[PDB]
Image (cartoon, rainbow, N blue to C red):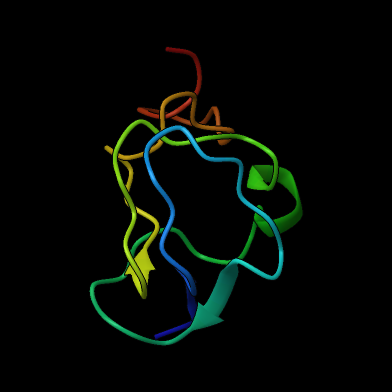
Amino acid sequence: NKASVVANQLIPINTALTLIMMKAEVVTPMGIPAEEIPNLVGMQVNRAVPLGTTLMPDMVKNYEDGTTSPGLK
């Protein structure tokens, strides 16, 4: 329904994310929404993210949204 965050360029494992890298586009699969765009920025991932790769929950190491499953590692 809404636009999800997808990596515009290709980044290796453990790479800091930036605003110009994360793109809020409405494409599948629906990974992480653009709610914590400025918050997730700076943190690195545990898996590799090629071009046009949506933000996945398993790819993020320490999730910033501490609601139910995501939160502290």
